[PDB]
Image (cartoon, helix red, strand yellow):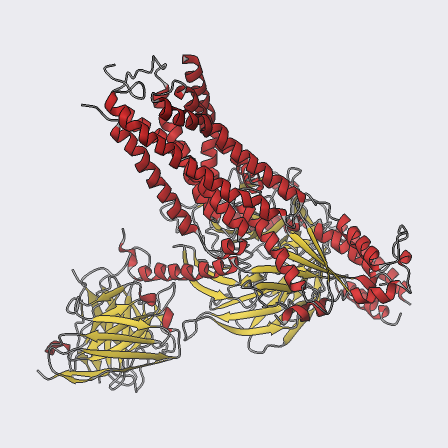
Amino acid sequence: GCTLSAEDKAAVERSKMIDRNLREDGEKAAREVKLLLLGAGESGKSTIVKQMKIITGIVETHFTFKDLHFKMFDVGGQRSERKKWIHCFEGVTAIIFCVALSDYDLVLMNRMHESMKLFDSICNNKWFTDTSIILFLNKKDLFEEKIKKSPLTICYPEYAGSNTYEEAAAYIQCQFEDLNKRKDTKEIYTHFTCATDTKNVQFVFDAVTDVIIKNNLKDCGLF
Amino acid sequence: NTASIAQARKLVEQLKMEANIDRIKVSKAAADLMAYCEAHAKEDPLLTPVPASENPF
Amino acid sequence: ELDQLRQEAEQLKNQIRDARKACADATLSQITNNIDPVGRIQMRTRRTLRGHLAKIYAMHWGTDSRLLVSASQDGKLIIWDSYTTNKVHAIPLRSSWVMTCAYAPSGNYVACGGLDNICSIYNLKTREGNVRVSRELAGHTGYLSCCRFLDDNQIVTSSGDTTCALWDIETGQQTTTFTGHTGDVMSLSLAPDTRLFVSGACDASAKLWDVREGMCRQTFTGHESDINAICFFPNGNAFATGSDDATCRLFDLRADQELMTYSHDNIICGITSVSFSKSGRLLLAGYDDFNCNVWDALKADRAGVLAGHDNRVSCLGVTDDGMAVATGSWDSFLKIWNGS
Amino acid sequence: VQLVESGGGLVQPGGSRKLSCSASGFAFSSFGMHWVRQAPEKGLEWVAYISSGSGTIYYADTVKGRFTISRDDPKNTLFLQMTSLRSEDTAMYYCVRSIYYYGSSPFDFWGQGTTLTVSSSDIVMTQATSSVPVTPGESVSISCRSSKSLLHSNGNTYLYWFLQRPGQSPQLLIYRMSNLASGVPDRFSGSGSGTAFTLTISRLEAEDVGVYYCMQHLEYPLTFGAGTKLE
Amino acid sequence: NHWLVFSVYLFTFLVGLPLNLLALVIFVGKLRRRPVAVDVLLLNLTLSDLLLLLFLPFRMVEAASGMHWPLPFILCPLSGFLFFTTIYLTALFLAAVSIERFLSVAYPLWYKTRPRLGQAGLVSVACWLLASAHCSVVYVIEFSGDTNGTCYLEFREDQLAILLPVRLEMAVVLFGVPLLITSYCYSRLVWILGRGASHRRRRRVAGLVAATLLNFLVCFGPYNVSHVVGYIQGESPVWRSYVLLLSTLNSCVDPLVYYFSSSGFQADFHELLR
């Protein structure tokens, strides 16, 4: 109506051009999967990162698997308050948790017991009340040579099962799954890793597809 | 130990620096605060809304 | 041994408390009970500002009080023309996880920082047409907070490593370091005179630091939890603090003690982004119940509620001339509030 | 930042020829580009302009519907083609860059110029003085007038001042009659009111003489001034 | 006779408007925040529901005096065209959203990567035009054979001769094909979700499948069975005032079944209410 002041005509269009770029990035962010990596101690985090990367803040990973660009964020390098910046990672596609099987013997309370409260806080967190969680049981090979010498009774006084991997690992997985107080809206994908038949990337891809189906169902009505 | 002594001494010194301050009474500070608030009341669009025609937004 | 040193520190704290209580003849509420109240306030939003796709944590318009810097979790810094609802620049950030923005008094520099432990300064008025990272500053072992702009060459920031830093723009090295906090440090509002500044830690402590001397001068403890907001009351003799519990506290500078607090039983959520008007009559704070609250900063009583938002309000500020109030929440929406 | 143009020469009337302007040192894809023609002895004149992203394209009244323009951002080049040339198109062509945002400086940097030869309701601007002697140390004033009020209903004016050195391309001096250009000495200043603008030079030194041009930017058919020469 | 029609029609008019308008508001907001392929289809279906529920009251308030029209004859064509178009548009649209849901379930990466918003808009407009033209043919043919006259009762020889084939085509094409398509697309929705998934997922999706399929069957069954019966019998049924009545109840059940369909929809409804 007021001739738009001529130069402002070239200004708003520039803003529109920025919009043309902005959504172009936003849509690019829509088709990108973001995953969060956590761990109490070592938990084989470096081993997992090195294994999945071949295919002082946050060590992002740009690896891709079957036309799906996965984003991996490491937050173990920050020594500060956890809940101050834990709301920034809400809305991620999935969260990957790493724990060590051979941590029930070492102390500094054992390391696995220290990881239990971290897992409970993460699973019961308000910001992560609708995000699927992936749990990795690292150091599987160390458990084979440790369970025979060190009995499991030290970490679990209420355990009386057979001292076999197929039973102790199942009991540990069940104990980790018991901490999910919101199982009616979240699921835990528990997997064991080893330095052979690298299906861990495939397992993460399958869990990502499952949670993507969940999110699409949420968007598309049913469930 | 030999490390906590230095931290305790630093804390004691820091408290010593702020131990003596020529502070004023709370009543006088509050009076100055309200005097400043009432001095710029007419120039504050938040308290006194500006006319729509002169409003920039 | 450390036992006698601890006893001496406790005695010094007791003496400080006694001196603080000595100068408590009257409160601010009694003085202000005889003054005219602010009355009903019905500020409404007249702007759209729809260009973000993530949660916003950005304020500090600048001296011109017309351009507003904005950042989100998508790693984009957008300069908004508030008058005409326009985008000036779109700077792609290397780190997508950022919560810090400054516009500098000169208006030709934009500073950002976050969990990358990196303070990035970008030049605006350059010969080229793009926005270049003027400098990268490192040396913090925690998530960044605030990038205040002492001068065009000096910038003061805080981190989660319980330290505050003051760096030089020309030389990417540490210049002044403050280490007196036991918790994460945010809320670094840079005074009305820029000669001083305060830092609100996560252990209910607000500490004032000398820029030139580099040592702490005053410590204020009146909260029961972490403090995540601050202002400076542009008069320059007081500052407001906001905590994760639904209360705000006004700490006087010369009196070195709390004057009064704003709280209500109807609110339980957190507080962020405490700002003051150009006269100090009003206090605006973005609460965590999806709306902002405006309190009368002199007596106690509330002034208004700004409910024009869908998510939790994270950033909130007032222009230098006090014309309008900018508010940014987690719904990727920026709103501008004006009187009528 | 550098702008270099090519495609000049002598061409018979009625022919077609293209000029290529290549930029090295800034972001071409986000800048609007203008073409300005200068007669051998007369003042500067506007030709055409293309916005960033090829959104809005405008041409002069005398060249509307005949000339064509285009850009290639990946090649960082601007092409302008002319068909059916006439004797009035014999001029030096300058390819200039501009950006349009809040507090921007359009026409900040100009090109170099190409010699093109042929064998055989608009707002106007007039300058009262075309030539006046100058001295190294005295203050001078240059007046420009407009047929329409350049004070738009937003609070700013759209005047520009350009200096052409004897042998160099025109360069911006001040923009919007109130803001100083980047890299220009503080001696130059501008002021005035609606339809009457003035430019003051104080503490003038040597190596600054040339031709002064005043620009209006109210509506796209930009028209140059008459030109003021100091010697 | 009179009671069974007007009482239920006024009940439908009283009930449908509020939740349908709130559904419009919530879906407008949902498209405002971020648009998906199914949102535009759902909003178009709900606005077709508005168009039905705002123009059927005109045919409702006459006391249904012997199926006689006191208002001029010009309005029977428009009212019938709009009403039948809305009914058949609902049948096209839930099949379309069934196709979209099956595509999302079977190929999650295909749904996530490709922005099918434009394709969703094209599908919606294509179904709009198809239903409009199809239901327009019927009332264009049923215009004239040459208080005084009425609409949708015992017709004449020339009208009845042409009405039966197009009505049978309507029942076997605009209903049978969408029903077969939605069954075909929805059969694998549970089959794919069965492999490696939680029991609550399968339970909820199966319950929603049953809800939608039972809604479609109960609402659009008697109308179409009377439709096909009329072709063999030859005449026009009398339970048309009844079976069509059931279809009207569908206009009241679409917003409700949609409200509990999505948890995000429930949360948005809970928080947006003032």
Image point (54%, 60%), residue name: A32
Q: Residue E133 appears in which quarter of the rendering? A: top left
The answer to whether residue D51 is visible is yes
Q: Judge from the rendering whether residue C18 lies leftward or rightward of residue A89; answer left or right.
A: right
How many numbered callouts?
0
In this view, E148 is above or below D41: above
Q: Judge from the rendering whether residue E247 lies leftward or rightward of residue E67; answer left or right.
A: right
Residue C24: horizontal and vertical position, in percent? 73, 48
Q: Nearer the viewer, residue C285 or A64?
A: A64
Residue C26: horizontal and vertical position, in percent? 69, 44
Q: Nearer the viewer, residue C101 or B14?
A: C101
The answer to whether residue B42 is visible is no
Q: Judge from the rendering whether residue E98 lies leftward or rightward of residue C239; answer left or right.
A: left
Q: Residue E74 appears in which quarter of the rendering? A: top left
Q: Residue furthest front?
A: E232
Image point (58%, 42%), residue name: A223
Q: Judge from the rendering whether residue C79 lies leftward or rightward of residue A91; answer left or right.
A: left
Residue D212: horizontal and vertical position, in percent? 24, 77
Residue D181: horizontal and vertical position, in percent? 36, 73
In this view, E236 is above or below D42: above
Q: Nearer the viewer, residue A79 or A114?
A: A114
